[PDB]
Image 1 (spheres, rainbow, N blue to C red):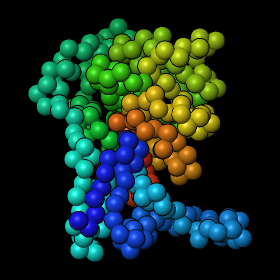
Image 2 (image 1 turned 45 degrees about the vertical axis):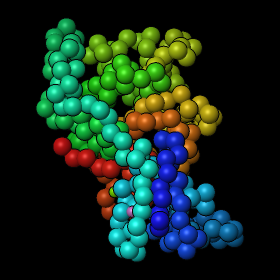
Image 3 (image 1 turned 90 degrees about the vertical axis):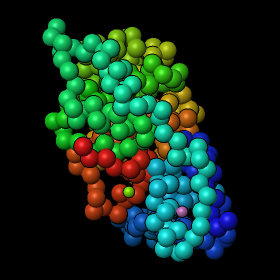
Image 4 (image 1 turned 180 degrees about the horizontal axis):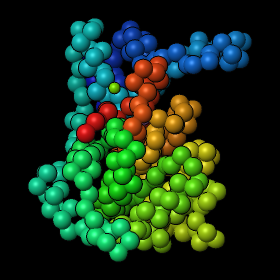
Length: 282
Ligand SMILES: [Au+]
Ligand SMILES: [Au+]
Ligand SMILES: [Mg+2]
């Protein structure tokens, strides 16, 4: 018909349409880069200072599929969306709660229970596969992240990539996961600076934890091994980092951004939902 959106791995979807609608879509999914005018690619090169999330390969970051409806409504377009794109996890709230009740989570030697909002956030994320979980730094996000990784670990064979803001937090995240008792250290590889003690060299570990600066220096192919990826404080991530590894996560069915400070009024908010999915506030 007018627009046909096909599945194309878990990083992007492919759009089929006319050359005319393509240019409309290309302008629609673009934004002004902050600081262009100082960029020599604009001052002397072929760049117009705008970031295009829809490339000429007609590929659009997965997380932005939902926004295409805004477009089609505006230009009166009719579109078919590959059903595989809107696919949700077959997990009923009933079975989720059942799954949660079999877990024995701890805090030192004292057993603890996740809060209702933590349970809701985890459930929302799993069912919908990818979301920007908008929760306050107090929402004890490490447990939300631990539950999300545990779930994936039990149901899929890939690996889990967790991106944190600093090397100190890399160690803290790994320690938290083990304190909960949902994971053991042999199961968590820390990469980069505080990258495990001399302990690493554990490339069989399902969970990989690092910072953006380390992660961005990895080969594109390195990201194919991940089925789930999380970035705590995703509002601190740059567009350069995101656009740098997004295509590499072609098998990353689950993707989550956690943040209490979203960039609602920033021009680039578009590429955070393109990388992490729609926003969800508990
Ligand atoms: Au549409
Ligand atoms: Au974010
Ligand atoms: Mg949005």
